[PDB]
Length: 551
Ligand SMILES: O=C(O)/C=C/c1ccc(NC(=O)C2(NC(=O)c3ccc4c(C5CCCCC5)c5n(c4c3)CC(=O)Nc3ccccc3-5)CCCC2)cc1
Image 1 (spheres, rainbow, N blue to C red):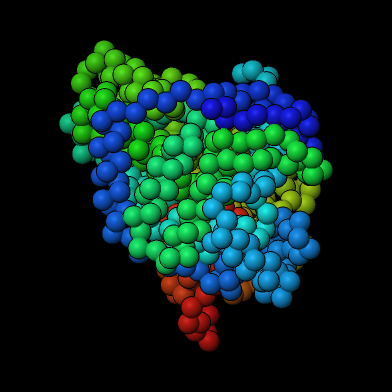
Image 2 (cartoon, rainbow, N blue to C red; image 1 turned 45 degrees about the vertical axis):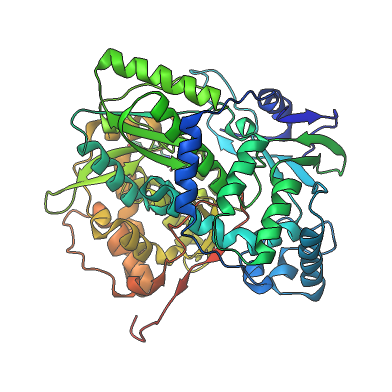
């Protein structure tokens, strides 16, 4: 069947930002018929995944618990209420949610309406390698349906992927644990070979059978009878496909592939990618495979069989993936150094702690984080990618010297250090106070993230070249600015002094002895590196359990 069918109505609007103007180019790439042939390898992996899913017990969320997961600026319902009414448990919001739920239990077939929209994402215009990227498309149901998805499936999508995939499930790891996983897998092989597999338009490669196969896995959970019916009805009415409506309310067409804006997008994509990849590893006869899967993002670390044999087995792996309806964008390339593998737009790098001990860390090319931070500094944005980048890439030279220096001086100037901001962590929205950054970093990356030095020449040159390309002042200017930022933060005491002393310890001539922050343990990070929720409309406010008077 065709992934999409179009009426002809436009996808109307809601260095550079992507807009609805380029929607046509995206629509052309994502529209095609899918050819899928399954085999014994696929059926075997599937049964093994289901045997693991069978250990899961999922809870039905209450209306109140589902409403509390809703982002404050989540798109309003077409039924006379918004995200604020949902979060406040307004009678009108709650009544409509209960009627949407009742309708899921009673109606098993009528397709549910969705809105199709162009995503506005910032990228860096580089005329050296082609041109501009067309806008990505987002497909999502009404607010009432999104609350019902949480009730039926939040606990499933949060618990099931790790139980099924175990250590292969990428979203259970903090950046440091991901690095630890990849390094341990690499060191465990006699002669290691790794590769990243890039599926061309993954969401569009997802068939209605893949969506039913994914439901067959959810159905292995112990579920409340209403959760079991809601999952069944949501599968047939929403997940498998349905009609598309543009921002103007016009019939835009029809979808028979993965919706990017449903609660199950990340879980379904991870399970599907893993299933197809694990089966393709058997068909390719790859030896001692270790996989790391994050939605459509796949990395495979295996045992090398020789240079020519590795190239041959990768072409065979690709053939199997293609039969399973997952053909590649860029064909996969065998790598023999762990640092050369780009996965989830990131790579492993190593540095030293204050004692000369080696520390592995996750980094990436800083162009897109710097261009997005420049955009966010220029105009008010709903999400602060700069904050999420500081959190995820805290050990990096670029996040420490540039992002921390720039943003802490702006916050000092605006007197907004305590003002909570929204950022995305594995697709989920977190409301975080910049004053909590030292404690967050210590908890995720360890105390060493504040003492890292001996960065690699390759990483230093990538950062320096990027600063030059973007007209950003060089590293020595940042060191000078961080000294003043640090002195002003130290002068304020409390959490602000801790920001100065810990985040900017790299900036001083004579480096301080840093002891662990006592209040860091109080932070409730329980929901942090559990699962992926990209397009899942998930929100959390950072909380502190058991506060001591003196902190
Ligand atoms: O000794 C030497 O050899 C060099 C000395 C030297 C060179 C340039 C400066 N620049 C500045 O002072 C100013 N800009 C900056 O001090 C500046 C700060 C952050 C900047 C950023 C990002 C970096 C990440 C956080 C968000 C801001 C960008 N650009 C920045 C410029 C350059 C810019 O204007 N825009 C972009 C566009 C895309 C990406 C980055 C940038 C402020 C007043 C005058 C212009 C200062 C000193």
